[PDB]
Picture (tube, rainbow over the protein chains, first blue to last red):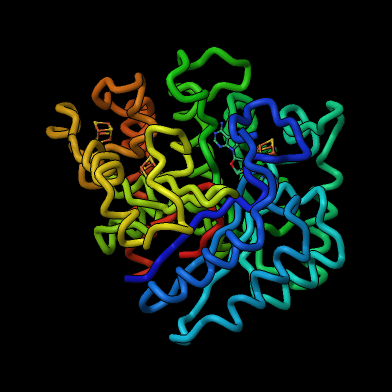
Length: 361
Length: 10
Ligand SMILES: C[S@@+](CC[C@H](N)C(=O)[O-])C[C@H]1O[C@@H](n2cnc3c(N)ncnc32)[C@H](O)[C@@H]1O
Ligand code: SF4
Ligand code: SF4
Ligand code: SF4
């Protein structure tokens, strides 16, 4: 089968201090021997194609020469002539001409984190000193357009986002950003939910989804296509019965998260000792996947909540992402935290989602 | 299937 990895080449290391972030133990920068062992194993084991996605942490802290070495390894060690996909998620604050050229020439797909216009973005996305970052992220987008880097925007949805969907959507529209991914702001794993100023509560999320869908659909009607990852996945589920977004298919998959020391985990939300599968230097990808830890991680997500069983939306929703059901350590999974939001949203949007699905055949 | 924190096109 193809192989897809999520790599943290600078570990959890980051140059910012975003208020909601729980991703920034740092294993430091991935060493060359780990990088080499990882790239060779993937190219030897994968069939069809493989994908390397660089995340963190701020992955550009690994430095350009790390990524240059990566490309050289891919060039030399792809004995099967697999297709290779590379991608990078970045805060954009360190992007300069050298990065933009590299990313463009090497066909990376880039995800740039931008939470909306200046005020909405800076409220949470602050630097180490507590200062603003929006202008530096705009500069990154500017460099990406200049050098034709393919990029999507990754926007975290906080309570403030829910109150200002008009400003956020209009800003991205003004900037001609056509590929958007809205990520729910999660409270830290196993903490009491909804305790922070930024916390995205179910009633905030319902409001966000309904208003976003309205702006998206009005555009659709007017022939302006805007790709919104969640709505695309619903469309996929409607037309094909499956989605290419993890969290939308009802059960978990092993994401092969590789930390900078080579340790491997099943999902970016669960880089914890109890889910450490082993080390990529010493195990095959098959062996990691077939661990008792991975099998257990996945199988836990197969439990269907009783409310879901009789839910009219079950074939559309599937219970949502396991991370949003995991309220307490080693307690069984609960109903999705956002269950009420999906129900209220589906009642509001489903007729028009079908409308769209028909028109894209 | 990839998670929504990773950039992807459908
Ligand atoms: C933390 S970052 C790592 C890559 C890079 N530092 C960046 O900002 O894009 C990965 C993505 O997850 C998002 N994220 C951070 N904290 C989150 C939370 N509590 N809930 C949901 N998404 C979050 C970030 O905004 C970013 O869009
Ligand atoms: S830039 Fe990314 S990794 Fe860094 S603190 Fe903000 S969300 Fe977290
Ligand atoms: S917790 Fe969510 S994102 Fe992680 S593997 Fe499970 S469904 Fe996918
Ligand atoms: S909307 Fe709620 S009850 Fe229905 S499938 Fe989704 S999580 Fe389950």
